[PDB]
Image (cartoon, rainbow over all chains, first blue to last red; front, side, top):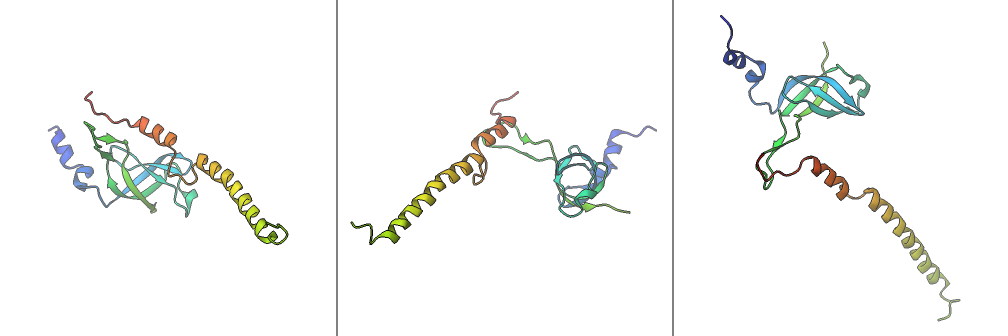
Amino acid sequence: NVESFASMLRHSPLTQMGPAKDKLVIGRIFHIVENDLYIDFGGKFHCVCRRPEVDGEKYQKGTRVRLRLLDLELTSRFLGATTDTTVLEANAVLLGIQES
Amino acid sequence: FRDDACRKEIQGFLDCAARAQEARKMRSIQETLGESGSLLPNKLNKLLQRFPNKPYLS
């Protein structure tokens, strides 16, 4: 009675989410560069969001935040290209901090 | 062509050139800095070097 991969995939939160556009997700700040916050939210790629002007000092490494997802992976095919160009990061909007 | 009667206009022409002469220095400084440019072709080309167009298969 070993669970199959097809079963794991069907019942994963990422599969159950459906499309990612305009979906609220919880992220975690794992890397910070100046006012650039690198946030992991459970997907393949992280998103990079600028430090908010209000309560900027509350956003630190490990701080859990609320995001509105736009794309899991930013990719596009440009004129003459044989494959899609990927920037290797997700597109998301940082809304604020998640609190209990 | 008697400068005694045209002192006000003469000074005005000299002020315009002085302001325009400094405008040569101000624009040049901003042109190199890219204050008005969206981005500098040197800066915009380093960014494209990292994401080169691939018209071939690898």
